[PDB]
Length: 309
Ligand SMILES: Cc1cc2nc3c(=O)[nH]c(=O)nc-3n(C[C@H](O)[C@H](O)[C@H](O)COP(=O)(O)OP(=O)(O)OC[C@H]3O[C@@H](n4cnc5c(N)ncnc54)[C@H](O)[C@@H]3O)c2cc1C
Image (cartoon, rainbow, N blue to C red; front, side, top):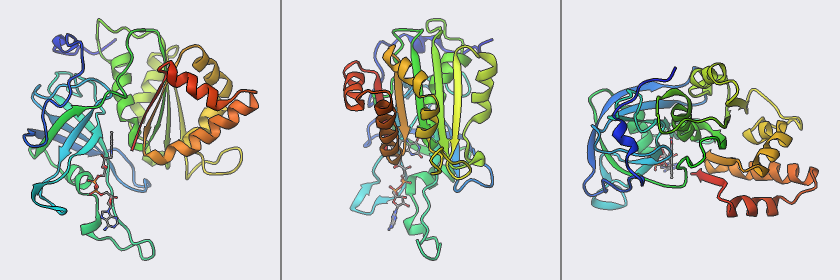
């Protein structure tokens, strides 16, 4: 049974909030918790950050928060750092089910000399390390929310949603899936098919795996979940197993769902897309279809949702 969430007045707004806080006057939020999401064999750290916004910075699932890390802009003396955007990984109610917190899924950007491996603090990512280094009680300059590309289409509560993530691109889908399956939201009762595909480097790099696996047991007729591990698995051609390769294992089912009106979403680092497009083109060709024409139709019908970075 679904978890009680409050306050239900978060369902009343008819439009998503946008730019509630702007960079010149951010909202000063407070860190609740920071935890690593990954095990010792992961190539780098990805963290889950819970942020208390006090109900002052509400959002809809699929939106992003901006964070302004501390310090001066190196390219602009006397001026703050540029905003960095992070897909919100929580529902509008947040991980405490109270409408006061939101969560981020943050990959630490670390520099290594391509020959020696030697680090250099001046070359680390500023905001990602700032966030993953944070501790309860620390203050965060929050902006936004922003973005509409990844809003969840709720007009059809029995729609099909095919969610394609790599790494931190899982973030919006954690929010979608909690709203679909975990939370007691009386005005959104999902009875369609949600299908999550997740590509990461290895088993230790999985993100929220226990949560997603539990949906298989709770909603076996409404949720599917497939994973790819690039460094621990190979595709049928004997390249590294990427999220495009798991899609190909379900070629027929996927194309049938798209033809029936399914939404398909892509999120994560933009390098994921070339290989996905290559696979989809080849799958279409094997079926005797033109991927160009299919993609044009999916775009025209508003079924195709991409937020990569
Ligand atoms: C819509 C959207 C959603 C996003 N969602 C997420 C998300 O959920 N999770 C997430 O982790 N990220 C996400 N991102 C990316 C995020 O916004 C940041 O770009 C990212 O976290 C890195 O920012 P940073 O401040 O750490 O790096 P920056 O300080 O901006 O540095 C960028 C890169 O340059 C490198 N670098 C800096 N100086 C040098 C140098 N001299 N030589 C070589 N390399 C150098 C850094 O190591 C880093 O790898 C999203 C982006 C967008 C647009």
